[PDB]
Amino acid sequence: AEPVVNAADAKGTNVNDKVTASDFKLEKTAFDPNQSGNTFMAANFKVTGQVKSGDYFTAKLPDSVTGNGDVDYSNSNNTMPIADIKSTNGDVVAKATYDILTKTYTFVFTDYVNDKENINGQFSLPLFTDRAKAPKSGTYDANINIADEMFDNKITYNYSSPIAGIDKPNGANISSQIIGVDTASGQNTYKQTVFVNPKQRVLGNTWVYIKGYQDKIEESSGKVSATDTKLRIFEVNDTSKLSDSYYADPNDSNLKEVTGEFKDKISYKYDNVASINFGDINKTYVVLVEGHYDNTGKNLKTQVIQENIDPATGKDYSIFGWNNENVVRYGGGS
Ligand SMILES: [Mg+2]
Ligand SMILES: [Mg+2]
Ligand SMILES: [Mg+2]
Ligand SMILES: [Mg+2]
Ligand SMILES: [Mg+2]
């Protein structure tokens, strides 16, 4: 019924003891995740002695990073296929997979390895922030491990500040980030975080539009509707505790869900756009969007917008918009 386990894979025997990594290098130590910024890690590796088909070795990510970034594999067993290690002749030497939960790569050997000895090679992998564990702009410990060898590192995330808007006390202010996109399962879903009035200004007759396209509706795979979209809305207690990474957890104590108070305040009157009547609001809110994209293949392009006037004077009308873009593209399914 219950047995002890040490890993998340099926195969022969782990051979970290036979694999030594070397010349470990990050393409860079600083980038803006909020601008589709990322890095790659790359290393040489060698097998001392012999291994066989089904033996494997591993690499582990720290809290600061993910192997998958904004690509979601919930609908694929939280498992993200990786490109294979191939030989000059073209033959696959190892099959690669990344467990999202465990932030662990696994490389399994193919029958290639049987009749050979003292394999050497190198590989690179993309690396992205962990929006959840690296929520704020700053410098994190990024010590990566390979074949049981720790390669100490440090990454700096300069997240474009999600606190953006019209520079005036009455100013319209808003922003968003799509931090989650399922491109494998075929369900075509995404997660977008929207920060409303992150200046925590007092704004009247405030309207917010979440568009599933930007300029030209034809140019986006975005599908915003009653049927395609689910919205959750939270008042923010202390806007100071909002993440630069747009990661927001519904169960956060800093959030107070209010989506209920919005029952008849959300409209889909317009094609591919969700209109939200906030009205007079004097604080910051988070909208968690769970959305869908179409099979067109077009980039998922989005745009969030907020407008308002002075609640006391009804003058000083202000409008502010924020754009979002992601690649949903995939190859062949059947
Ligand atoms: Mg080793
Ligand atoms: Mg999909
Ligand atoms: Mg209003
Ligand atoms: Mg509509
Ligand atoms: Mg205004």
Image: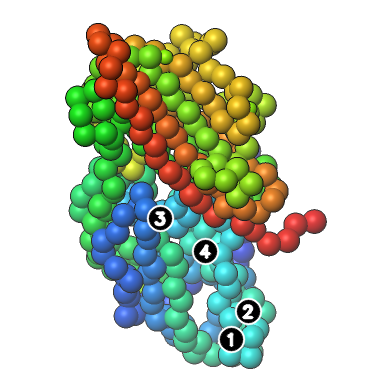
Q: Which residue is mark 2?
A: 92
Q: Which residue is mark 4?
A: 106
Q: Which residue is mark 3?
A: 36
Q: Is residue 74 among the parts visible in the rendering?
A: no
The quadrant in which residue 317 appears is top left
**In the rendered structure, which amino acid carries the disc numbered 1?**
Ser
Confirm or reject: label 3 Cβ below 8 Å from ligand 2.
no
Q: Secondary structure at mark 2?
A: strand
Circle on res. 87: 1
Q: Secondary structure at mark 4?
A: strand
User: Residue 270's spot in the image, x, y percent?
Assistant: 60, 27
> How far separated are the C-alphas under marks 4 and 1?
18 Å
Pair 2/4: label in front: 2
The quadrant in which residue 310 appears is top left
Pair 4/1: label in front: 1
Placement of 128 over or under 288, stated as above or below: below
| Residue 15 located left or right of residue 20 | right
| Residue 198 located left or right of residue 168 | right
> How far separated are the C-alphas under marks 3 and 1?
31 Å
Q: Are marks 1 and 2 in contact (CB under 8 Å)?
A: yes
Q: Residue at x 64, y 85 (%)?
A: 90
Circle nearer the N terminus (1, 2) = 1
